[PDB]
Image (cartoon, rainbow, N blue to C red):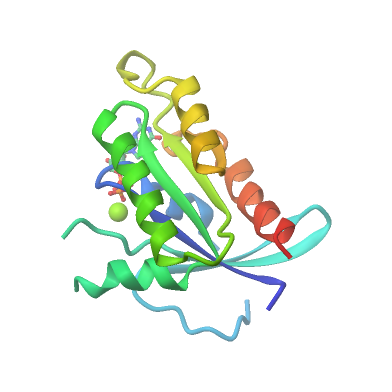
Length: 166
Ligand SMILES: Nc1nc2c(ncn2[C@@H]2O[C@H](COP(=O)(O)OP(=O)(O)O)[C@@H](O)[C@H]2O)c(=O)[nH]1
Ligand SMILES: [Mg+2]
């Protein structure tokens, strides 16, 4: 409870949420019995221990699970694919949706452009991701979950952001 961070992955189908979540996990004694699509890992960030509870239960078709995700997170990773415009536009919709669900809280958010390895398929530019993050007042990163590029920096980044709002 200060050492602990509940982090929620949201985004359109096929953007890479589950692939991100799997890289994050892999290998004790947190109080929480993990359910559905929940992962726990304890991380060292800036010389301080961080227990992350990661939720990856956002699907596009349990309808209440959307409202659940939007309510329980301390922090959010709003994921789109650089090779998919509509997922990028969806990300803005989800950010607005999240802001309405949490009107009075300063929620740490990272906007994540996944699939950066798919160079010839890029449809969304780095500048667009950046400009969008500026409009949203959140952070931005591009990852490739397939090759584990910037995935470490991402989860360090989100812990770093939630600590700044204390
Ligand atoms: N090339 C590439 N493929 C990816 C990346 N991340 C995920 N994928 C692929 O995209 C497909 C759907 O990914 P998934 O993680 O299930 O998306 P989800 O719906 O958001 O959970 C899978 O076949 C993954 O192999 C990435 O960074 N690069
Ligand atoms: Mg998934």
